[PDB]
C-alpha cells in the first residue's frame, strides 16, 4: 500500500496515526526524536516507529525517500527543513500550519520538484477556511455581496469542567493565553479599518452570543484584514476574526494586569522559592502577608466592575494560592512565575472534556437588495479515554488531506491550501461522513 | 427474592425497572393501564408486566398483596389510592412526590398498619434535601449558624443542544414552564420576608453564576419560606429556592406577555386552523399579515431591553413561524395555541442530551464570628441511546430508597421523607458509589 511518515509527538499525532493505520493499505511510520515516544505513539496501532533528528539532512532524506508523503506535525520553524528534504526526495508533504515566509521562498522549487505540499488544513487554519470559502462562493455565485464576515473560535473546557478562575485549562503553557488580551488588533468595521492598541484591547472584550447555554466573551485577533484578499471579499464592510473565552476571563486578566503580574521584567522578588504571600507583599508593597493587607494593596491598584466581580476575582486569587504560604516556582519575573502557578493548577484531569467552538457569521446583501444573515457553527467535545476535540479537529482534516494527496484527489504539484471549493468540497464531505465533523449552516430567521 | 411493583409509564419508569430488575434477588412487575406499555417497559429486562386500573380498589389490592413494596410513579393525586391499598394489604410504598394533604390525613393509619411510605426521594424533592440537610447538620454540629441558604435547580438542554428561542426543550408540555414567570414568589432576604407579585416576577430574573461555561438566569420559586422549618434554620437571614433557565428565556417570555400571548381567555381568533400570521394580525390589530406590519404592532406593545434583544426575540418569533402561513393548532385561546406551537417545535431529537443542574449555596457564620460560603453542585447530562438526566436523577434515588425499604436500611413504619442524616447518609453514599451521582462540595476560597 501507501507509506505515510508522521513527524510529531504532540497529542495531535495520536488520532492521525490511529485513523490512518486503521486503513489496510496505509503503512504509517512514526518519527520523533526518541525511539520510545514513537514506539508508544505507534504501539496502539502496531505502526512502524523510528527516532529522527529533523536537522540532520541525511537522516531526514533517508526516511522521506522511504515514504510517499510526510505529515509534519512538528513546530512550524522546522517545516522548511522538511520541505527542503521533500524537494530533494520528491516526497509530498501535509501540514496544519499557516504558510510561512520560509515556505514561500521555497515555492518555485516545490513546483519544479513536482511535489505537493498541502498546508493550513487543521482546525484554525483548516476547517474554518473550508466553510468560509463555501458560503462566500455560494453568495458570490448567486450575485450576492458579502457585507459582513464575523468569525470566532475558542478551545475551552466543556462547561461542566470549567470551574476554575479563568474558565480555561492549559495543555500546557499559559503565557500566550494570558498575553493575548494585551495584543493590538486590526479589522474592518462598517467600511473602515479599526485598530485597537495593546492597552485598549481589554475594554473591547464583550459577550458574544452563539447558543443560549453558553456564556462566551470575545476579543478580536491581531489582524483580520488579511481575510479580504484571502477570501476575495473586497465588498465586505465588516471583517472580524476573534477568540472565544468564557465570561469572567478578561476581568480576571485585567485585575492581574493592574497588579503588574503580566510584567516579564527580571525581578528578584521572583528569583527564589519564597511563599506567594511574601512575593505579593514585596511586589505590591503590601503592609504584610496577611490576606487583608494583600487585598488592600490590590484594591488600591485595581478598577473593579462591581462588588460581585471583585469578590469573584479575589476568591480566584485565593483559590490560586496567591494569598498563601505555597512556594512560588522561582522563574525570576512576575509573568512567568504567575504562568507556572496557572499551569500547575489548571490542567485537564482524566475524566474531564475539552471543547472546540467555531462560528462564522455572514451578513449578505443580495442583488435585489434583500439582506440575510447566515451562521455556520461547530461545537465539538473531547472524549474521555479517547481524543480531545483539540486533537481530533486538527488531526482528522490532516488525515483526510493526506489520503487525498496520496490518491490524487488533491491535485498538485505546488504549495497548496484550502482556498477553493475544488480542494475544499471533498474534505468537508469526508470530514462529515467519516467523523461526523461539520459546521451547522443556518439562516437567521 | 423480593417482589417490587412499579406503577407508572413515564420516562422515569425505565431506569428504575432496569436497575432493579438487574438485581437477581428482585422481581419487578410493571403495571400501567395497558398491558402492552408494561410489556414494553418490562421487555428490556424481561420483567413481569400487567395492566392495572389504580381506581379499582380490588384490582389494586390484588397486585399490592403479591408484592413487598410498590413504587408509585403515577400522578400524585393517585398516591392516596395506592396508600389506602397499601394500608389494607400491609405493603410498603415509595414515591418521589411531595407529601400531600391527602397523605397526611392517612398518616395515623399508615403508622397503625405498620407500613413504611417513603416520600420525596427523586431529584427535587430528594437529592436536594439529602445535601441540604448534610451541610446544615455539619454546620449546626460545629456550633455554626446558617445565615444564608440559596438553592437553584433547572432541567435544561445540554448547551450544545440549546439552540432554540427559549434555550429550553419540552417533554412534553410547555404551559407550566411559560406561566412560571407569572407566579408570585415569597422568600427570606436579609432578615425579612420579600414577596414578589405575578406582574413583578419577570423583573426579578437575573444572571446566576455557577461555572464560567454556563449562561444561567434565575427566578425565585413560589414559596421558599417553608425551608426554615423543614431544615430547622431559624437563624437564617436569607432563604431562597429558585429555578435556572438559560440567558434570554425571561426576555422572550416577557415579549410574549406584552403581546397578550399568555392569556388563556376563550378567544375566537384561535378557534380554527388559520395561519399564524392571520391569527396574530387579528390578535395584535396589525395592518396586515406582512412581517413588517406584525412587527410594527409588536413594537408598539413591547418594551425591549436593547436592539440586540429585540432582534433576537423577533428572530425567535420568525423561527417559531409566528409570522408565517403555518396553521395554528386551534386551541381556542392564545396561550394554549402558543403552547402547542412551542411543544411542536421544541422537543428533544434523538442525538440530543438533556441536563440537570442543582446548586446549594450556604453562607455560614461560625461561633468565633468567622464567615464562610460553601457550595454543593450537581451537573448531570443525559446519555444518547440511554436515560435522560431528568429520568436518571429521579429514578436512581427512588430505586435506592426502594432497596433500603426492602432490606430495612430505611426503618419504619411511617410516612417518611429524607430529612435526617440517618435516612439520608446511606442514600447519598449509594447514589455516589453505584451511579456516580453526587453534589461536589466546595468552600468558596
Image (tube, coloured by chain):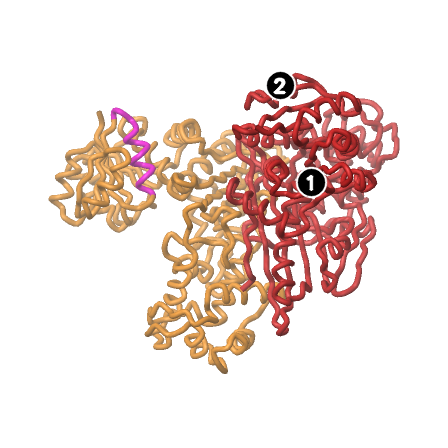
Chain colours: A orange, B red
Which disc is residue B39 wearing?
2
Q: Disc 1 sits on a residue from what chain? A: B
Name the dominant secondary structure of the magenta segment: helix
Which of A160 and B139 lies nearest the eye of the viewer?
A: B139
Q: Position of residue B266 (x, y in %)?
A: 88, 31
Q: Which residue is mark 1?
A: B118
Which quadrant: the N terminus of chain A? Answer: top left
Label 2 or label 1, whichever lies nearer to me, is 1
Disc 2 is placed on an element classified as helix
Point out the residue furthest to the bottom here: A287
**Residue beneath the point at 64% across and 24% down:** B30
Q: Is residue A129 above or below residue A169?
A: above
Q: Residue furthest top?
A: B36
- Measured as percent of width and height from the top left, residue A438 is found at 46, 33
Q: Could you say where residue A20 lies in the image, as x and y percent from the top left?
A: 30, 31
Which numbered disc, 2 or 1, marks the residue that appears first in the sequence? Answer: 2
Residue extending farthest to the left is A58
Residue stretch rendered in magenta on the structure: A12-25
Instruction: Name the residue: 28% across, 49% down.
Output: A75
Residue nearer the viewer, B270 or B139: B139
Q: Quadrant of residue B146?
A: bottom right
Amino acid at each position: 500500500g501507501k507509506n505515510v511518515l508522521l513527524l510529531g509527538s504532540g497529542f495531535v499525532a495520536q488520532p492521525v496515526i490511529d485513523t490512518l493505520a486503521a486503513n489496510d493499505d496505509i503503512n504509517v511510520t512514526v518519527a520523533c526524536r526518541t525511539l520510545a515516544n514513537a514506539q508508544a505513539l505507534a504501539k496502539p496501532s502496531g505502526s512502524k516507529a523510528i527516532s529522527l533528528d529533523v536537522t540532520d539532512d541525511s537522516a531526514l532524506d533517508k526516511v522521506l525517500a522511504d515514504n510517499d508523503v510526510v505529515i509534519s506535525l512538528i513546530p512550524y520553524t522546522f517545516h522548511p527543513n522538511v520541505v527542503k528534504s521533500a524537494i530533494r526526495t520528491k516526497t509530498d508533504v501535509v501540514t496544519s500550519s499557516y504558510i510561512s515566509p520560509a515556505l514561500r521562498e521555497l515555492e518555485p522549487e516545490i513546483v519544479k520538484a513536482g511535489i505537493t505540499v498541502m498546508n493550513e488544513i487543521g482546525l484554525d487554519p483548516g476547517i474554518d477556511h473550508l466553510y468560509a470559502v463555501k458560503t462566500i462562493d455560494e453568495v458570490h455565485r448567486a450575485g450576492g455581496k458579502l457585507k459582513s464576515f464575523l468569525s470566532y473560535c475558542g478551545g475551552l473546557p466543556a462547561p461542566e469542567d470549567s470551574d476554575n478562575p479563568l474558565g480555561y485549562k492549559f495543555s500546557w503553557s499559559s503565557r500566550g493565553v494570558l498575553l493575548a488580551l494585551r495584543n493590538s488588533a486590526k479589522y474592518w468595521k462598517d467600511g473602515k479599518i479599526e485598530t485597537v492598541s495593546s492597552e485598549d484591547l481589554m475594554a473591547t472584550a464583550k459577550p458574544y452570543f452563539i447558543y443560549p447555554g453558553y456564556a462566551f466573551v470575545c476579543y478580536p485577533n491581531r489582524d483580520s484584514t488579511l481575510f479580504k484578499d484571502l477570501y476575495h471579499i473586497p465588498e465586505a464592510e465588516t471583517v472580524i476574526r476573534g477568540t472565544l473565552r468564557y465570561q469572567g476571563f478578561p476581568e480576571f486578566v485585567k485585575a492581574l494586569v493592574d497588579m503588574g503580574m503580566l510584567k516579564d521584567d527580571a525581578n528578584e522578588i521572583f528569583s527564589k522559592p519564597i511563599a506567594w504571600n511574601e512575593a505579593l507583599k514585596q511586589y505590591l508593597g503590601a503592609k504584610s502577608t496577611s490576606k487583608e493587607d494583600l487585598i488592600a494593596s490590590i484594591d488600591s491598584k485595581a478598577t473593579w466592575k462591581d462588588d460581585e466581580d471583585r469578590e469573584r476575582i479575589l476568591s480566584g486569587f485565593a483559590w490560586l494560592g496567591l494569598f498563601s504560604d505555597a512556594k512560588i516556582t522561582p522563574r525570576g519575573n512576575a509573568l512567568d512565575t504567575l504562568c507556572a502557578r496557572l499551569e500547575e493548577l489548571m490542567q485537564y484531569e482524566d475524566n474531564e472534556r475539552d471543547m472546540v467552538v467555531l462560528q462564522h457569521k455572514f451578513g449578505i446583501e443580495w442583488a435585489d437588495g434583500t439582506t440575510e444573515t447566515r451562521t455556520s457553527t461547530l461545537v465539538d467535545y473531547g472524549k474521555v479515554g479517547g481524543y480531545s476535540s483539540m486533537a481530533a479537529t486538527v488531526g482528522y482534516p490532516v488525515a483526510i488531506a493526506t489520503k487525498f494527496v496520496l490518491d490524487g484527489t488533491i491535485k498538485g504539484p505546488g504549495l497548496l491550501a484550502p482556498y477553493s471549493p475544488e480542494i475544499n468540497d471533498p474534505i468537508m464531505k469526508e470530514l462529515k461522513d467519516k467523523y461526523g465533523i461539520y459546521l451547522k449552516e443556518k439562516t437567521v430567521a
